[PDB]
Amino acid sequence: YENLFLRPACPGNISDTSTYNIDGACVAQGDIGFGSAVQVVGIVDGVKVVAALPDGGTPYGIAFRSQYEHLSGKILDGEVCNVVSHGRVWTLTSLGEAPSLFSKLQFGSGGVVTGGSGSAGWTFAGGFVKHEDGYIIEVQVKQNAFIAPP
Amino acid sequence: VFRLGNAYLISIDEIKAGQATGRPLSTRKASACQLAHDQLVNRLVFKGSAPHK
Amino acid sequence: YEKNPMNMSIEIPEAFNMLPAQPKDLHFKVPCTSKCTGLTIYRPMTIVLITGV
Amino acid sequence: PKPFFMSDASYHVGSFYNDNATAKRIVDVIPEEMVTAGFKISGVKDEKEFKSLWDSYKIDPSLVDALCWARLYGGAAIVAIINDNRMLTSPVKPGAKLEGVRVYDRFAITIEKRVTNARSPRYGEPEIYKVSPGDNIQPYLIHHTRIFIADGERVTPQMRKQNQGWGASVLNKSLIDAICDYDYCESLATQILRRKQQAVWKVKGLAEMCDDDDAQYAARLRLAQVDDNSGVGRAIGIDAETEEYDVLNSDISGVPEFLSSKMDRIVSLSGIHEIIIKNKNVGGVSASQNTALETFYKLVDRKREEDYRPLLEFLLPFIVDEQEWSIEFEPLSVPSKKEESEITKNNVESVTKAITEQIIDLEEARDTLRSIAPEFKLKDGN
Amino acid sequence: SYHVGSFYNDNATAKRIVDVIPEEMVTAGFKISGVKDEKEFKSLWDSYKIDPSLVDALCWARLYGGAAIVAIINDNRMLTSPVKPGAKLEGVRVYDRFAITIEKRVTNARSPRYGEPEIYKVSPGDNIQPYLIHHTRIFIADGERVTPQMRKQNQGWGASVLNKSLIDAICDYDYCESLATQILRRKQQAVWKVKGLAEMCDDDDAQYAARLRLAQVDDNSGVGRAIGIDAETEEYDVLNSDISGVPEFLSSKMDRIVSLSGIHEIIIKNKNVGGVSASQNTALETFYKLVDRKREEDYRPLLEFLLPFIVDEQEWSIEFEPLSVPSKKEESEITKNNVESVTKAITEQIIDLEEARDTLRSIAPEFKLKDGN
Amino acid sequence: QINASYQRDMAIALPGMVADTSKYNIDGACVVNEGDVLVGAAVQVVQAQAVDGHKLVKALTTGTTPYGVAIRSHWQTVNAQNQMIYEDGGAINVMTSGRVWMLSKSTEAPTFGSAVKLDVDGQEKSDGTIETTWTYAGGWTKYKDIQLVEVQLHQL
């Protein structure tokens, strides 16, 4: 009774076949890069409008890699977008060394992981590899973890 | 009138696994469910259920 | 306006269809999809819009 | 990590087939021969009008391509419309009518109705089919009598039930990657040929110039210019202290044998043999391609009996009005004037060499003579 | 290793070794003697069209070591009770090894049927209740012979043809092919010596530019091209290795596959010998020998189980047509020989027309004839 | 004497109707106790049987802790007061996770991602006294005189 692993290990894709959720009814304002956190700025007709994470926002999900929706290499303004709201996913990071297992991550500007000492939110899942003179980490996203401030 | 139900789990590895003699694990797990259903019917007849009136 | 497909069009690459039902514990889930593009006006100046009527 | 809208094996196998020529051959080189071989029917009053109806209806290319996708996609559907005064959903009463035939691939057909009545032995099979071609036409419903489903190869029941009772593609993963490795080996062979010989030129101080400089550009231009003009009948001068010019070389051997072994694996894994898939005669023997071709016809017949005939009893009763008939298949053997001349002389002398003293009369002698298909015309008569 | 289904539906060699025999065996055909005529027999046979069921039934019987078939008869009784004598049926269907079990045991002293199960329970699934079947309606097909000290452990059922020896023989072949591809890839190597190259710290634009330069330089090397180097600092060398004997090694592996299989090369490798013109005929007749030898032991019981439910005639015999590929010219000549043999010298003795004609169409001719005197 | 055409739109939500086919989880091994509940209202658990395993649920009251929201079902619900309810002594379909449309008593649109607060009778309210951990999913609509909001729930 076990969960299979997923082989390609690139940023912006899913790392396991555990319970995951993909919110595919969204549109982008500005440009978004695969493997970055996004935030919900508004809702029109059951569609969520997302943008790259600013300072002071609450992350909602992580952009997901697809080879039909995004032929350019990144997500462009006015495009339908895939966003992962629950599951394990490879994220871009600016950190230098792996944090403690099962710690709480903190997101800098642009939707990159820079902290490992948060109070509550998403947690580190134990994966840490290297990409392009930069690193990739593995994050565990949960649905109601970050709550929008009143 | 009321409805009853349960379920069971089995894995492909245990389906692969063979035994010297005896009924297969899947058959035993399938018979257990029927026995449980019959026992629950008997218990409902002879003991009742307060929340279900 | 002048009704002629050489001037404006609405195109439906894929019509309405229903995917096979996905079973779960005691229910089913039936999805459906379709494709459309909207109105494309290849040759403008053939349409006059009188506003404030 | 999969899209919900529809499967992707469709795109994979379709693109691979329409791209690679070996795929074209391996999935087309059987069915067209199978169908064009022809057949005969017995118990019928005459065959000239039978041929007239057959070639007036001319659904043979449709049958060819139907069997083609049945082999490739693992499933295909063929429907013949009948001339009757009933709704297409209703069943079909006995009769001999047909006016149109057309074929869809695996993806346009689904099940609608199922009955498990104990009385009939037909319980457990699709009663009604939902056909949804697309092309801005509403999906509609067809009775069981009107649809024939052409399947591929048998699979284990635990997978047959998972694949809604439908077979698999002829291109399994072992065949696919065996084909794929050929091109990689071919590219490696071309690279090996390219890298046979290498010339190197060492001059103390070439490291001193930094990148993107006119001196370095001139030096490399001079190198290319001089390397162009070297050869057997020309010599190149260098300086003893500051320059050296070396050449390195390597050998090539066994490459044709390695590719031959790869093709041997491909043909063995496919099941169609060399003089038809590689399309090269062995050349060292005069009369072994004859046994090769007879084995090929043996295999095509053994498979054909299992798939072609069901089309025959599905379609023929809709055009033949007689009560009983029989279907026979032409022996797959290329005839030849000469050999057909001797066989016909032997048959004509055997039919009347010794029958002259028995009750075997002309009315059955002519039937025997013109049953074995002769070139001797004979109109009906006494 | 043990999931034979994957081996069957993934590797084509297992598919062939398990499928090639039974389907050709059944499509060979058979003939019956003691019957008034054969036209009606063939008509009812191809009207019933049960041969796909026979094919795949024999297939899973060979593969899983056990299978069952049930033929439903047109009778006005419950399917548990036995049969009265008759010749009827309306359907035939097959179940694999896993859906069949013995239900009640008969060991009475009087009947020689003791030890032969009387009642079976069948559990197809498909949300329908498992039911009970009397023996007279079903015939169980097993695999190959095995010792009793495993026959009684396998609940009186045969064994799979895919024993572990054949399994690992098939397995290591792909290993050898992968190793051959690797050896071909590793034919030659190029080495670029640059003193101080280790001094660079990693994940830096310096080494990124260095490897980009390496790409640019090695992409354009060839026969008509030369590359400059600096003698004092760095050097460039090439080493190589040879390949030989790999085709022979692979051929030996395939020969072991065939030897452990038991069906020969003109059927497995599908490659002609080429050096001889008239030995493949003997190879194919040896194959025909083995297939007939195996057919006699299993295919016949199906026939004598099924025919008594279709034939009302009293006594009959079954003959297996000699499975040989016939041919126009040769069949024309053999018809010549037989037609002159049947009436060359019979004109002088009591062998008369009515038996002579019976003889002459007892051998299946291409010469039709109307029934009569 | 010219022809005409007209265009009309369907409503988009119903009380207790499941918002979409995303992550959801349904508890069907519960039984309603001491009264009846409303389709699209929060419920609370009194006790859980140790051996039998059936939970006992009732409508939310003051000082309690929510557990889930009853959902729509054309077969398990009974029709009273022109609406579907779950009468006493019957199996109930509680929802423990996912997005669902709930009856609301507020008058202004909520903020996406904010926490949900309820009334003492199990109906959402913008300034309720009962505090939960569920969130707003963005949806905000209105049927005929009925106010519905789209709420996202996670396992307790």
Image (cartoon, coloured by chain):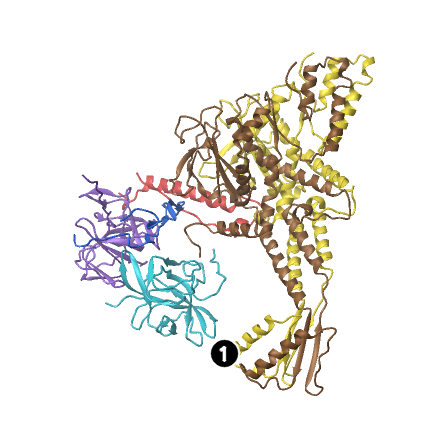
Chain colours: A cyan, B red, C blue, D brown, E yellow, F purple
Left/right of residue D347 with respect to residue C53 in the rendered view: right
Residue F123 appearing in the image: yes
Residue at the bottom extreme of this rendering: D241
Q: Residue E141 vs residue D294: left or right?
A: left
Residue at the front extreme of this rendering: C45
Q: How far across and how far down the image is residue C29, in percent?
A: 37, 47
Measured along the vertical axis of the image, is residue E244 above or below residue E122?
below
Residue F103, percent from left and from top: 21, 53
Figure check: E275 above or below A28: above
Judge whether B4 appears above or below D55 on screen: below
User: Which quadrant of the structure image shows residue A101?
Assistant: bottom left
- The residue lying toward the viewer, choosing from A54 and B37, is A54
How many C-alpha atoms fall within 10 Å of the one at disc 1: few (<14), some, or many (≥20)?
Answer: few
The C terminus of chain D, quarter of image: top right
Relative depth, front residue between D244 and E293: D244
In the rendered image, the vertical position of residue A91 relative to residue D54, given as above or below: below
User: Is residue C25 among what the camera can see?
Assistant: no
Drawn side of residue D346 relative to residue E143, left or right:
right
Q: Quadrant of the N terminus of chain D?
A: bottom left
Name the residue that disc number 1 marks: E205
User: How many numbered dots are placed on residues in this image?
Assistant: 1
Please report the residue visible at 59 percent of the width from the left and 51 percent of the height from the top: D21
Disc 1 chain ID: E
The residue positioned 78% from the left and 14% from the top of the image is E351
Residue type at numbered disc 1: Asp
Q: Position of residue E84 (x, y in %)?
A: 55, 21
Regarding mark 1 in the picture, which secondary structure is present there? helix
Most foreground residue, D42 or A18: D42
- The picture quadrant where one finds residue D238 is bottom right
Observer-nearest of D218 and E220: D218
| Residue F27 screen position, x and y as percent | 32, 51
